[PDB]
Amino acid sequence: QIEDKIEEILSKIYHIENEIARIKKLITNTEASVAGLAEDALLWDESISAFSASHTGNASKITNLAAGTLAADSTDAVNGSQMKQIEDKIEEILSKIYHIENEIARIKKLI
Amino acid sequence: QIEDKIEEILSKIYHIENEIARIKKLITNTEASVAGLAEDALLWDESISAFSASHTGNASKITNLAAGTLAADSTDAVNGSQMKQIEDKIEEILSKIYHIENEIARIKKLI
Amino acid sequence: QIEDKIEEILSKIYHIENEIARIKKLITNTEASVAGLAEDALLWDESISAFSASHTGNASKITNLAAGTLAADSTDAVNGSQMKQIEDKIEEILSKIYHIENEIARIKKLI
């Protein structure tokens, strides 16, 4: 029996070392995934009290951002499409103004 | 003694397999948390060189965003509340312009 | 031999318990890193169907954000620098308008 008992002790141990092998290569691909997430997630910076879009040495864009609600106490982020429509209306208004000034000028010439 | 030695060898092994049980159900709830974070964190996309707010098939909003600083080289994100005030002022200016054009029209009728 | 066999069984076990020690202090500094990432990553909130910049009790800023593209279907986030230029142009246009109204007023006084 005891040489049997020893046999079953080695069976249970060689199983232990292969359950451990599975752990160790596995733990690694997780510590790897955590490292990846730290580098590429947009993270809070406590030294500035804000989330920081710094990545690959500098300020970075955020894209694939859907339009934010335009309302009085909205906390939605706003996108360039939204901004473009504002920019467009501004350029129209500058042109209009110009032309109003010309007309005022013409009137002041008739008087 | 040797049947005692064998007893203490099995004591140390049945402890090993229950320290290992604790590891394996634990490692799982961590590989689970890492998977969750990958899916729901706002992450850098190297194919576009920007953080991407894509989620659940499409562009997504960002909300609970506090007002950004409006200054010359500000890198703060801006919110819809901010934008709304700009939109409001634009609508006022369009109305004013309209009305200026009417008045100019009336003057040109008196001459 | 069997007291040798027992010796080599204890050698393989005291190795097992120190490979396990390495695991357990290691797993901890990972479950720690996952907890940190959950707290400080900007994460999707399924109850609102948007990424949420809430952190340390309230709405938060996002900074170090590079300028977004201003174009018709842009999904880029826009920054305060961008917004400031819009704000500036608005303030110019209000002043101009004022002054146009004065001039219109003066003309209406001459007639």
Image: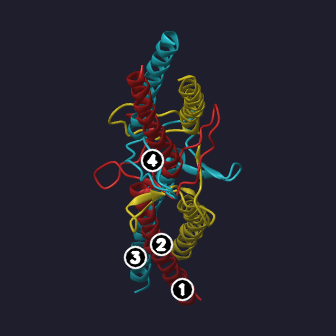
Chain colours: A red, B yellow, C cyan
Per the rendering, the mark at residue C7 is 3
Q: Which residue lies furthest to the left in this view?
A: A57
User: At 54% from the left edge and 45% from the top edge, which residue is drawn?
Assistant: A78
The reply to whether residue C32 is in sight is no
* Horizontal and vertical percent position of residue A95: 43, 40
B103 shown above or below C28: above
- Separation of marks 3 and 4 at Cα, in angstroms: 52 Å
Q: Which amino acid does label 4 sit on?
A: Leu
Locate the N terminus of chain C by quadrant.
bottom left
Q: Name the residue under label 1.
A: A11
Examine the rendered structure and indicate whether residue A15 appears above or below residue B40: below
Return the disc, 4 or 1, that comes first in the chain's sequence: 1
Q: Residue at x 65, y 36 (%)?
A: A71
Distance between the alpha carbons at the discs numbered 4 and 1: 48 Å
- Marks 3 and 4: same chain? no
Chain identifier of the residue bearing label 1 in the image:
A
Tell which subunit mark 3 falls on: C
Q: Is residue B9 left or right of residue A102?
A: right
Residue depth check, mark 3 versus mark 4: number of the one nearer the observer:
4
Tell me the distance, in whole angstroms, between the alpha carbons under discs 2 and 3.
Answer: 31 Å
- Which residue is the site of mark 4? A43
Q: Which amino acid does label 1 sit on?
A: Ser
Secondary structure of residue under mark 3: helix
Report whether mark 4 lies on the same chain as mark 1: yes
Q: Relative to C51, is C62 on the left or the right?
A: left
Q: Name the residue under label 2.
A: A26
User: In front here: A48 or A62?
Assistant: A62
Disc nearer the start of the sequence (4/2): 2
Above or below A54: residue C7:
below
